[PDB]
Length: 330
Image 1 (cartoon, one colour):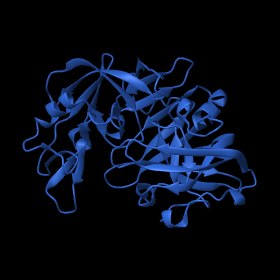
Image 2 (cartoon, rainbow, N blue to C red):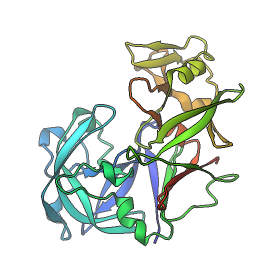
Image 3 (cartoon, rainbow, N blue to C red):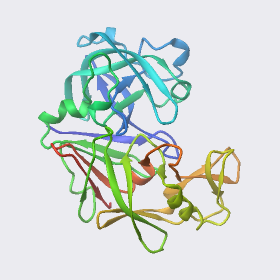
Image 4 (cartoon, rainbow, N blue to C red):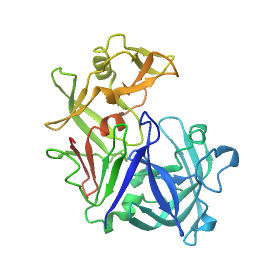
């Protein structure tokens, strides 16, 4: 089997991407944030504290003939941005782009933190990291990809995110029309539960390539590119007037600037992020200070190849027995 679904930016900055997912019988379609950096599928629901729902579409398990309470199971998760959610668990039928999983754990939120409430465009998350990170207790649950793997034509999914435009998540096949050149595959460590790999270096604009190993995660659920402070300083040094602001919380630059590209290495291959992809707009409405899309990872504990980097590539998440990542230009 295969599946193919379009993913759409939630706003004009590509702050996140939403993909329609069918849950239950008859189908209830919710727009979920596909997150290769976490492993829970959770939804706003009829159980979510009413004051914490503000425009989201909810899953109502009582209206699904295929929903079954997973008795005793609870979940609770906190994300790298300080947001969090928790609740109980049902199993139900979940389909993404024509690909159906029966018995998928659907984690129903009883509580969500303010950032989720305040974002009316995201109805929940669909985690695509390794199932060892799933938070359901006392019985850990598998991701949608893990459940579907055995049925897929090939045990892979691909992320093809758009710049200021929709893109595609495919399951079970590699669309050879979606990229240029060849796909370069690179080794993955699953030891932290992430799609963790090692970049071979970077360049800033037309500058020379610096060969240096950068360990990080391919994370579709993180907006920006978070790299070591040395790398980030080298990039922003090429933008007149750019500076790190503690009051804003990262590098800002004059909105009048033209940003240089940023290249990252995948083995001997090179992925080029155009400068425009690094512009996240005024820090506040009408400001002439703009927020940068490449930021320091120093406060995180891990480097994050988020959407800013991934949207410059066609990305293969290969879930074969020994997982690997593939990157192609497009």
